[PDB]
Amino acid sequence: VRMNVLADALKSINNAEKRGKRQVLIRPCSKVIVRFLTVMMKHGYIGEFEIIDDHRAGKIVVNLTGRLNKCGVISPRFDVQLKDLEKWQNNLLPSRQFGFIVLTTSAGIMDHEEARRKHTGGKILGFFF
Amino acid sequence: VLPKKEKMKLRREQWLQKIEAIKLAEQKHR
Amino acid sequence: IVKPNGEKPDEFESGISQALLELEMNSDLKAQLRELNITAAKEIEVGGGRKAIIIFVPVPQLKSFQKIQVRLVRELEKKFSGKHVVFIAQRRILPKPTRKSRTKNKQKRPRSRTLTAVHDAILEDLVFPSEIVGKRIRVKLDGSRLIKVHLDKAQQNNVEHKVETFSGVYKKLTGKDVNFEFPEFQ
Amino acid sequence: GRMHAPGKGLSQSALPYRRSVPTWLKLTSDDVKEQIYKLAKKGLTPSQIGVILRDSHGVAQVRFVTGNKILRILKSKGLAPDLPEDLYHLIKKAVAVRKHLERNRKDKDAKFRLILIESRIHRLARYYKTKRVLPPNWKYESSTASALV
Amino acid sequence: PLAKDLLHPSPEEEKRKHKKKRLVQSPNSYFMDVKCPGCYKITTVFSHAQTVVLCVGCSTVLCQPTGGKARLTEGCSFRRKQ
RNA sequence: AAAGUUGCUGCAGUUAAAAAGCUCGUAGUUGGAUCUCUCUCGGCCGAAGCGUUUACUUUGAAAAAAUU
């Protein structure tokens, strides 16, 4: 059955982007998915997206751009302390300029640079380069 | 056709070239 | 007619109370208005210099206000100058239960007392004659949301000119930008 | 996909985005409630109550008009059955299959279907004892099946 | 190919799609008023009704349930609502 | 150590080592969307109940040398 809706959203975005599509429809929506896509958006990777609202879990239309190589989820959401974060990026991002671990910390959902800037750790969600 | 060792070497090196191209493209925008 | 929760009548809501009384002693809206009452009122400039009237009514009488809404709106528009009148129920926002709060939360708050449910009810009550048939949220590149609201095509002509007043009222009361559209088919 | 069956159908109902009661419906919430009460007096489970109310009386969704759903309306009045309707239907089906088995012994297809139906009964009974709709001493037994219909 | 706006589908495309698979799901059914030729009373019936609907006074059959929509009796009139 | 030949990172199982007749079937593992600090006594504060309780993250104190 359907577990980890963020995994489905990111797999759908990845499979759409590898076919060179302009838009992708991802369902069901979630607040975690919206925060993840907002972090992905604010660095310039997925353009701009629109939430479609039914009286169910909603849908999202994401207007893909072409910059995205890979967006991925890490299941299960391992606890990431502020030291071990370096190990994690040495595991996940293949290059040290671009790529992003997305963390859920108590200060919100943000990227690993901002998580170091806030001097906090948390649980891991994904990465995108 | 050809052994897999240089196949993964070609894929890794082309991915390295792809990374360097993306890095220099993002560096040019500054 | 006016029964404020703070029990402080200002001149605006007392004036529209006199307006409702004059409406009752002349027009056919007689047998129902006595049983009813309002709570508060405000006046807001929207759309670049166009004023609009807001009347906060109590919630459990609001359904009855739905029965005489259009007649009350047209009679207050005849009474007033070029204006726009909206009836919005006075909903109570309960704060989100955290680990630092007052010791009054001995019972779980209802979902109708949350922020999102109250703002949905406010959006559906700000547009009474038309019914909301769709909702989109466009999230801009700066990260700021924008709600796009789809209303009835069938009764479009009633509220064609009030959509900017609706947007200004919702923006002033909430802080969220809202646009209104009409789909060509349902 | 289904819970025991391997099929995956899509046939279901699609509720509209308008939760509003339509203008053409002249029945009020109360009149809907007395219709519910009289149909419950006729001996009807909430499924046929909703079906008759939708088909003939023009109310699409009881929860949209009265503000509350049918089982809670019957529970407040007290005309609510001791078993939920689905468990009752499952038990009735088990009785009918067992009667057929007693008439026809070699019908091993019905034996397999009987095992399937009792499996559904046990899962649903576990759920109902979880949320205290059933008392915690409830147990399904083969000879204690015809007494519940 | 590879480029079509998902937020704004054409209405014939939305009509063609399965009711659950639309952008926002919406049913294919409707409520209609039926008038028996033997009387004047109007009755509200669901298009996909599963129950046989009888007239209040005439007690004639108004619809017969079938696999999909209900078969109204030859002679009755109807009008779709809203 | 090369070694991803013990595999959490990070392996496999059509034809090479290997996935069972099929369904039902405890435990365990996993699980859709949704909810934005105050009350008293003593000098704007100190004491007190904390707010459902946790898992998580951070800080501070404290934590042999030698070795590194």
Image: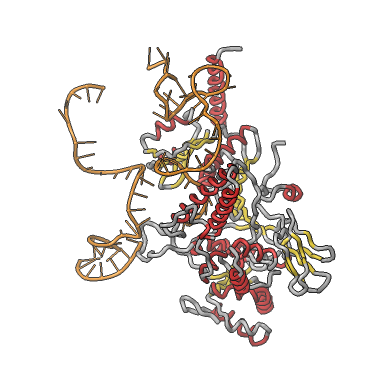
Q: Nearer the viewer, residue A117 or E8?
A: E8
Residue drawn where x is 52% and y is 35% of the image: A72
Quadrant of the snapshot with the C terminus of chain C? bottom right
Measured along the vertical axis of the image, is residue C179 above or below residue F5? below
- Tag count in the figure? 0
Please say which color scheme the image uses: secondary structure
Horizontally, is A27 left or right of E50 in the view?
left
The front one of C125 and D104 is D104
Q: Would residue A88 be found to the left or right of residue C60 on screen?
A: left
Left or right placement of residue A37 versus residue C106 in this view: right
Q: Position of residue C28 (x, y in %)?
A: 68, 84
Rendered residue at 55%/49% (across/down): D117
**Residue E82 seen in the figure:** no
Q: Quadrant of the N terminus of chain C?
A: bottom right
Q: Position of residue F35 (x, y in %)?
A: 48, 57
| Residue farthest to the bottom, as pictured | C25
Q: Furthest-top residue in view?
A: B2
At 57% across and 71% down in the image, what residue appears? Answer: C43
- The relative height of residue A121 versus residue E44 in the rendered view (above or below) is above
Residue C56 x %, y %: 55, 72
The location of residue C138, given as percent across then percent down, is 60, 50
Relative depth, front residue between C118 and D139 = D139
Q: Is residue E12 visible?
A: yes
